[PDB]
Image (cartoon, rainbow over all chains, first blue to last red; front, side, top):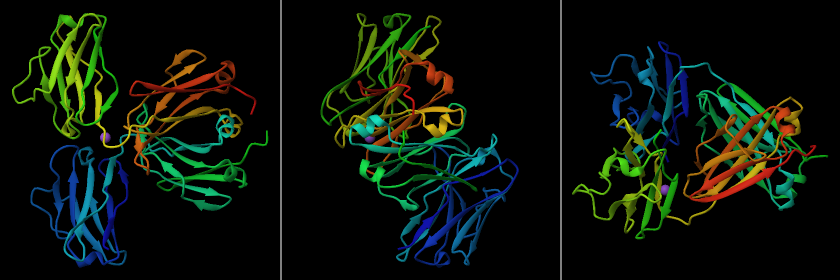
Amino acid sequence: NFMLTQPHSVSESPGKTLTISCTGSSASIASHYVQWYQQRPGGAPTTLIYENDQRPSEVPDRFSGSIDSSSNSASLTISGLKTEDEADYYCQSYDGNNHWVFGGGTKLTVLSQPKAAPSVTLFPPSSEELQANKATLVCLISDFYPGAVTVAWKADSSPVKAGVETTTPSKQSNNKYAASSYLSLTPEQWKSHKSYSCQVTHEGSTVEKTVAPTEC
Amino acid sequence: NFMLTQPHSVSESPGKTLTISCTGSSASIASHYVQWYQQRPGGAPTTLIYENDQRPSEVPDRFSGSIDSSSNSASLTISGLKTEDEADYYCQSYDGNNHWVFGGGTKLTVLSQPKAAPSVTLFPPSSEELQANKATLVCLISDFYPGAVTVAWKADSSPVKAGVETTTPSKQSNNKYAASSYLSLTPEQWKSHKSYSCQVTHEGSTVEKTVAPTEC
Ligand code: NA
């Protein structure tokens, strides 16, 4: 039935303005009231926006709500960004039976350092692995900021989904993020295809790397 | 100066008995009092044991602390593991100047599913990488539970710390955990050494793979 989708992450420098979206599925977003909550790490969530655009008195005017019926979305706009705004933000509404429905949440990053697109290194199966009748590709994703990427794999052009595992991005020692996606297959599938590809999307950046069985 | 070392992770089925050890370095464990704190996931830390073995009345008698001067260690024992005992555990004492000294912390898991040691797949630098005057080794760690590991690299037989980056464990789709570690070298250092090793520790069990520079 009805479900709410939010972006995983949003970013902006201090003093500027960003916006978090909340897109509904299977039903109109305008059918029920939409709420917005801020969740600092540990502690009670605070109500920022209720009934689409009404704001509690203790919430500053920087936070505003809106509803766009054209895109079936709710929007939380935050101006005059401060570092204290760094938190997780949730949108909430009701389904057909007036039962609660929440979004996945959005990590707000107040940019403290230069942005960085990831390095994408694709590894073919090691000879040791292939001697053990096993085959796994590893897509290493390193040195990106903020820490939100989506990975897509391809075999001989067509995309694959079965056998794909992607780890949650975690921080390296230089305050940048690292992650890795891996695709496990049988050695037959590995050789029965001309090439494999791993495609990483990081905001408006897309890198795709391609490997083929070794000829050496 | 004075340091306190705990195992990284421990686990056991409900109802059994488990001991977490805290070994001191550079000074005697019997010189100052030892505390044991418990941090449940997402909660505030509380005092389990203070002054080596004194127990606050609100703490169940299933907890107990001891001191062993022969091994220069303090130990927390939990008789009859309960589900609410799943938490992080810390030992704490003082140095010669009576400043706080904390152990590294131990993650305790009450087993809800079978324990599974990790698979460790070690990848050498690809040709596409060495073509670009770059070299990265990737250690893929997958299919383990509980989700807690520590990774250590070695060049030939000496431990290497510069260039290591390890990601945090992420829950795969089969309800087990995966993680990765990578070591970034120059193509000169890769060719110079005769072998590289990645050592993964999972609750006193260690898996360790080795690769050597072979042309292609
Ligand atoms: Na667990």
